[PDB]
Amino acid sequence: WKQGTEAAAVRSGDKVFFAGDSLMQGVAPFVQKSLKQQYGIESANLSKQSTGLSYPSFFDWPKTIEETLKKHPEISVLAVFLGPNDPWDFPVGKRYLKFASDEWAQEYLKRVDRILEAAHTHRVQVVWLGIPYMKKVKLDGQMRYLDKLLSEHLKGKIILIPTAQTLSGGKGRYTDSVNGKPVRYRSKDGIHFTAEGQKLLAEKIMEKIVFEPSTQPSS
């Protein structure tokens, strides 16, 4: 099944499902409110601090998504935002895979594909947010690697929303504030967002969600 790659369509009665770590936790509530007020569209926000794809033993996102879609066929959109908890070696069965090796990347993308397969089997449109620039230089290098691994694999398959340049006003690197008045989009920990940054990314998500009236499409 081939979803749209530019935007996701929602009809009355659809639900939007939000998944990911603390990056999603702060953004999703703003999108939930806009969906409800603008379109009457309900949503579920299951994002959870410290989670990711590398350690399903802590929290298993592929399995959670598989089970949520089975129980809630009214979900038509899955939005995903994660990354910063994942740049670590991890075990797989009998093996121990090292961060950014060929085998590590292959297993990481297999977990990504499991999420896409669950969604697409159920005709669910996937929206996936790119990883922001980080203030810590080592973490930023890990996230630039992971963001490129994900985007190279996902482009053309789903809807992608880059965040790094938007949050930096185009500077091509982490910034604390953006301009005539400076606005702070990032929190003091150099990873997460202020309320203004959360709202900005929620607006970027809403640009990718298109309400479909009952008289569309036309014959």
Image (cartoon, helix red, strand yellow):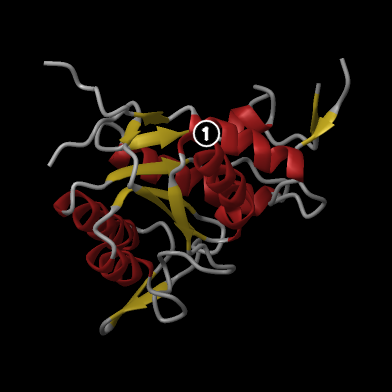
Left or right of 27? Residue 215 is left
Q: Which quarter of the rendered picture does the N terminus lie within?
A: top left
Q: In which quarter of the image is residue 150?
A: top left
42 above or below 197?
below
Residue 97 visible? The answer is: yes
Please tell me whether mark 1 sits on a helix, a strand or a loop. Answer: helix
From the viewer's perspective, tell me whether residue 194 is left or right of residue 207: right
* Quadrant including the C terminus: top left
**Residue 67, image x and y in percent?**
27, 70
**In the depicted structure, whether residue 183 falls above or below residue 193:** above
Residue in view at x 32 percent, y 27 percent: 213
Q: Where is residue 136 in the image (x, y as percent from the top left)?
A: 71, 51
Residue 178, picture quadrant = top right
Looking at the picture, tell me which residue is in the foreground, 40 or 139.
40
Q: Where is residue 176 in the image (x, y as percent from the top left)?
A: 80, 37
**Residue 131 in view here:** no
**In this picture, residue 142 sits left or right of residue 186:** left
Q: What residue is shown at x 56% (from left), y 50% (from top)? A: 28
What residue does disc 1 label? 38
- Name which residue lies at 55% across and 64% down: 85
Most extreme residue toward the right, as rendered?
A: 181
